[PDB]
Amino acid sequence: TSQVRQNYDQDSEAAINRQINLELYASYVYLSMSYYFDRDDVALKNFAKYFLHQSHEERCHAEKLMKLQNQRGGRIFLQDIKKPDRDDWESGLNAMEAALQLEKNVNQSLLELHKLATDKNDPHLCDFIETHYLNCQVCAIKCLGDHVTNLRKMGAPESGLAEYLFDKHTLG
Amino acid sequence: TSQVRQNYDQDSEAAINRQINLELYASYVYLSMSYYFDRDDVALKNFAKYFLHQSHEERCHAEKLMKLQNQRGGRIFLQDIKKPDRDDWESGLNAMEAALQLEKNVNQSLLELHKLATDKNDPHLCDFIETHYLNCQVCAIKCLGDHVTNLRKMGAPESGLAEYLFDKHTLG
Amino acid sequence: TSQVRQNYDQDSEAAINRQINLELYASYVYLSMSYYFDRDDVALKNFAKYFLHQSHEERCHAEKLMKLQNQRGGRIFLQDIKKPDRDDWESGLNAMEAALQLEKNVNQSLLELHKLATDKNDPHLCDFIETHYLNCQVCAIKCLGDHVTNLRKMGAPESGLAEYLFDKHTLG
Amino acid sequence: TSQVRQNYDQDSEAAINRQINLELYASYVYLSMSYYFDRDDVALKNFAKYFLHQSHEERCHAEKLMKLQNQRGGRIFLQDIKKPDRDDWESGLNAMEAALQLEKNVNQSLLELHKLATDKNDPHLCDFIETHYLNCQVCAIKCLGDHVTNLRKMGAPESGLAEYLFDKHTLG
Amino acid sequence: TSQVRQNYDQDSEAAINRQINLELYASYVYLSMSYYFDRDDVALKNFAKYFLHQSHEERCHAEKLMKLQNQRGGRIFLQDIKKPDRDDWESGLNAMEAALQLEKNVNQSLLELHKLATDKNDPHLCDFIETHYLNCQVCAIKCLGDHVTNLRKMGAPESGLAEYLFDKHTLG
Amino acid sequence: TSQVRQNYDQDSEAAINRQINLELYASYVYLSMSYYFDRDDVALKNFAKYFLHQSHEERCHAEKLMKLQNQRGGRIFLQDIKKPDRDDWESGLNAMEAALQLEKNVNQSLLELHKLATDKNDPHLCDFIETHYLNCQVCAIKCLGDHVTNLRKMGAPESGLAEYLFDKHTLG
Ligand SMILES: [Ca+2]
Ligand SMILES: [Ca+2]
């Protein structure tokens, strides 16, 4: 029993660890996407920068989660960070849609965590998720949807010119 | 179905569209009050300025609700903006009292909305309402309450001097 | 009867209240268009930004009209603000063509209002309309005409790439 | 009843009045600790400084609570501020453990207050607690837990050298 | 016995502790007074602002007093801070009068304390009272007395306008 | 076959992927150590900062490796990032020694990679490792050895004061 623990359910704790790993996984996915667009045969520096930044963001969420854990007296338990589903992300459009899912998936997990926080009557954990994740996710998912829409309407992925311009005008 | 929609109930979506219209309405009411005090037979520039500002506020609130709708993949449907209940707001004290009532109504509407978001377990929608409207409405109610009270004690509406000085000292 | 009223015919008064409402209406159509381009499935930020500005400009025109009413002793009477024709504006080209028409209509109304002022021999009303409205109308129409022409030549609406580039190069 | 009152339960109101007194009590407890370390036979200026600041923090919370009460239409009702249960706090480590308990009790109390807020469907009062008190208490309990862990691991309270160096290196 | 203690009579010590509780009490009276004018049905921010300041002042005095105690070798013993008389101060003029009284009582107590220090031939405790409390009280009294005069003369509390203007012109 | 590939052996390529994962693993270890010292029962902010920074460094090496891979035409293949051996790092000293090994181990891998680069006569890959890793490793291993030595000589881990001071004077 931690001296600072208070109103922090066991389910909550395990769930945060569950969440820390998921965030790290998302991060790992993005890192993968990033360096795919860095390949001499894909060559889209901005898509590359975009994802690398997205990757670093997920790592911050992960670290803020670990912070939260220690903050409420819970104990951190890391677990293997599973590698990404793919190695080759096909195209800019395909990668964007993959991210759209990744985010919607992490959002699903966040909402479930919030539901558990509510059921366990842990307002502090609820506010933490409300203020630091929920709203960011909606923004991110919205951002991705938009990029996907633009890429689709520009003629991607068949059109290489489309992905090129998008790289320059939206991600640049 | 929107590619970014997730955990967004149709009722909530319809409720947001309702709120949007209510905000546009409130904004119309304040616009009306504003120019009332701009009449050559009322001539209270600061009351006029105060309400014009309030008007622009409610319109900013409307646009933020519309932004919300899109962010969560809902679809906006505008409806007529009914006209204010009057064209003559009588006195400054009277318009202040009406605003107090208009705000408490709008707030009432937001409490409905927030309660709905809860029943439909939509934490994002609840935090949006919390962190953006519920807190601002309370401050607003309190402000109007204060103005209403000051106007009454100074002698309004009976005393024309009262409203003149409140115009200069509180609204100027 | 206002103490400042002088040579302000009643038909003029009513014509102006009607214009105030027409202006507010235009502001509404524009607000509607702005947030259409904000939809995750349209996603043209500069179009959204562009029309949101025109909405603010039209609203600002309404208010000057309201200021004018009070300047010459007239009395303001507001009416409901009818909802825009559509909820979906299709494409950039379509919204542009729609906006061009809207503009020509308001102008159409201003011109009649000026023909009335001329008939009622009210030089002040004529000058207020010439200086503050007719010029901006000619300008806005030419601006909108040009936009429409560009979009057509680029291949819009069929060319999604056309609307993306226009969004970035002309509206950005 | 207040003209601004809206969705503010009687029980909630009384709960605040209660919390207001609790915060003042905390403030008093810290003020006592503060000057205990200011005694020539204790002599730890930074521990003193630390608690004197915590003391002012707690009073500020009380004052913000009183603001809330009038902000929603409630009515402040002050009660005697009961003196702390101790006059001599033995040591820096002992005092820290005391503060830790005092904070977990204030937090325990805010959580009950937040519960009540939810049982009464009062979302405003809910965000007010989450945003201005819930995270603050968590961060504070963590800080105190840390301080207690360091002091113990340093040799306190047996070692006078230990509390001295903590006074200089952690609180200075 | 304290190693720093010198020429500090046990009665002086007990009187200093009594004074500490008294300054803290006064402090609590002003705090109560302050938020009374923050009420939506009183609404006089500068009165509220004014008394809040006087409140923080009283606490600074209480704190300096506690510092004196330790400086001389005495030992602090806190007592309950008894709640103020009223919960409703009726009017600014009334609150101002109550304050004038509070100050004259605190003063009476200080003068007593000074004579005690004199009979106990403790010049240090005499000069401390002279320099840091006595002239401050005289000023406070004269200030409060002046405020009462203006409020009575402007026509308080019958005239709401009287207190409103005093709020703006003297306390603003 | 990549268009930019040239003098880049298959063994080399696979070895770099091998290395990328190792770097990411090291990074993961450090992240773990970092947040262990953030626990309310360990409480050494600087050891915490130290490792978190060390962690971010290993992630840069990882990313620079992925960069290298694409640079020479090789293809990146990520793999699960195995979790750290431990969850509880016992103490500051124990963590330092663990890092000393982690670094010596990563150094062993780097030297082997360099040997392979030499055998495959790939000077570019040799210089890359010589300039970007070999020298840094020697510095890091030296740094860790020193910290270990200091902690040992100060009385760590039995002495909690030792770890405390070290945290403040060397890591701060
Ligand atoms: Ca002209
Ligand atoms: Ca919240």
Image: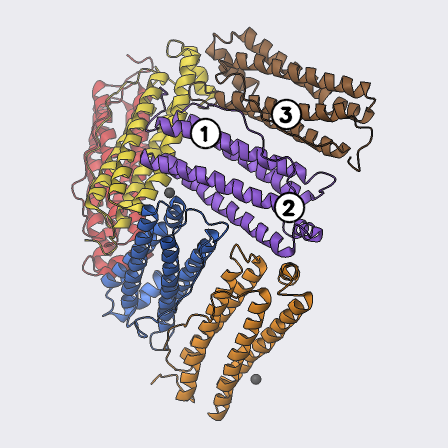
Chain colours: A purple, B blue, C orange, D yellow, E red, F brown
Q: Residue at x 41, y 17 (%)?
A: D149
Amino acid tagged 2: Gly
Quick one: label 3, few (<14), some, or many (20+) residues within 10 Å? many
State the mark number for residue F21: 3
Q: Which residue is mark 1?
A: A18
* Label 1, label 3: how far apart the Cα atoms are: 22 Å
Left or right of E22? Residue A166 is right
Q: Secondary structure at mark 2?
A: helix
* Label 2, label 1: how far apart the Cα atoms are: 30 Å
Q: Are marks 1 and 3 on the same chain?
A: no
Q: Nearer the viewer, residue A46 or B36?
A: A46
- Residue D152 visible in this rendered orientation of the protein: yes
Q: Position of residue F74 (x, y in %)?
A: 74, 31
Q: Nearer the viewer, residue D51 or F162?
A: F162
Quick one: label 1, few (<14), some, or many (20+) residues within 10 Å? some
Q: Is residue C131 above or below residue B71?
A: below
Image quarter hosting the C terminus of chain C: bottom right
Q: Which residue is mark 2?
A: A92
* Label 3, label 2: how far apart the Cα atoms are: 25 Å
Q: Are marks 3 and 2 on the same chain?
A: no
Q: Position of residue C73 (x, y in %)?
A: 39, 82
Q: Residue at x 22, y 39 (%)?
A: D15
